[PDB]
Amino acid sequence: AICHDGKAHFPREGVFVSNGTHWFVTQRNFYEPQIITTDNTFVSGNCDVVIGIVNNTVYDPLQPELDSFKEE
Amino acid sequence: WTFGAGAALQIPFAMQMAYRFNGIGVTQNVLYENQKLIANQFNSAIGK
Ligand SMILES: *[C@@H]1O[C@H](CO)[C@@H](O[C@@H]2O[C@H](CO)[C@@H](O[C@@H]3O[C@H](CO)[C@@H](O)[C@H](O[C@H]4O[C@H](CO)[C@@H](O)[C@H](O)[C@@H]4O[C@@H]4O[C@H](CO)[C@@H](O)[C@H](O)[C@H]4NC(C)=O)[C@@H]3O)[C@H](O)[C@H]2NC(C)=O)[C@H](O)[C@H]1NC(C)=O
Ligand SMILES: *[C@@H]1O[C@H](CO)[C@@H](O[C@@H]2O[C@H](CO)[C@@H](O[C@@H]3O[C@H](CO)[C@@H](O)[C@H](O)[C@@H]3O)[C@H](O)[C@H]2NC(C)=O)[C@H](O)[C@H]1NC(C)=O
Ligand SMILES: *[C@@H]1O[C@H](CO)[C@@H](O[C@@H]2O[C@H](CO)[C@@H](O)[C@H](O)[C@H]2NC(C)=O)[C@H](O)[C@H]1NC(C)=O
Image (cartoon, rainbow over all chains, first blue to last red; front, side):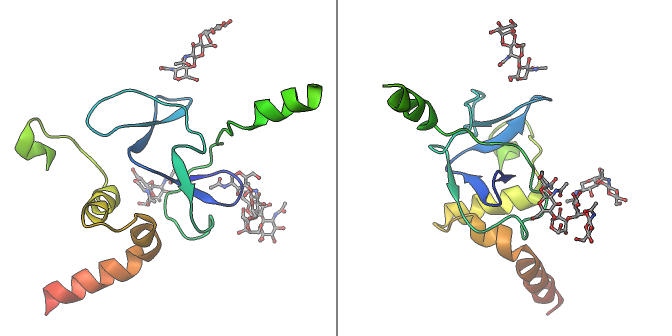
């Protein structure tokens, strides 16, 4: 899994992998990395139960639009 | 099951069980939140 803000995010379909510095989510039968965002994972529960959870961040697609929206 | 289709690929057992649960139509969070209960039930079953 993965912890961002106290909420554990799981992959909609695929697995989390890391090349050594960054984490990605990829389909199971073929290697093609994808940046992990809110469109790949769904929240459930909190960070205090899962075993082996990791501590990387998760992107949000809507943030840049707000900045432009505030700009104009 | 990858070793039945081709070369053998390693995978943690918890993740494998999550795959199976997804197979029978149950989200993964159930397994990742009840791991201990499932393990105890399995051990007791083999003992019986
Ligand atoms: C991922 O990265 C984030 C960075 O912020 C970490 O955030 C953590 O969030 C926790 C709150 O949910 C903080 O505390 C957590 O919950 C309990 C209360 O603190 C406790 O079980 C842990 O906190 C202790 O361990 C942390 C791990 O380093 C310490 O940072 C933290 O200061 C606590 O250390 C002592 O704990 C005892 C008991 O609570 C206290 O009596 C002491 O006073 C504490 N010492 C000091 C100097 O304060 C648990 O983390 C947590 O503080 C906060 N930061 C960290 C590093 O944990 C996530 O933990 C991190 N997750 C993973 C898997 O890396
Ligand atoms: C593992 O994946 C990470 C992805 O974050 C790789 O990060 C890599 O970081 C370097 C440095 O930025 C990138 O190279 C280039 O750097 C120049 C610096 O100016 C920049 O202008 C380029 O746009 C580019 O960022 C590299 O692209 C980037 N790679 C990826 C896939 O994002 C990291 O290198 C990977 N490590 C291994 C061992 O695979
Ligand atoms: C996954 O396996 C690794 C070992 O390869 C475990 O890491 C160590 O396990 C021993 C217990 O025998 C501990 O004494 C060490 O403190 C562990 N080292 C670290 C960095 O954790 C690891 O515990 C296993 N992962 C889980 C969730 O149990």
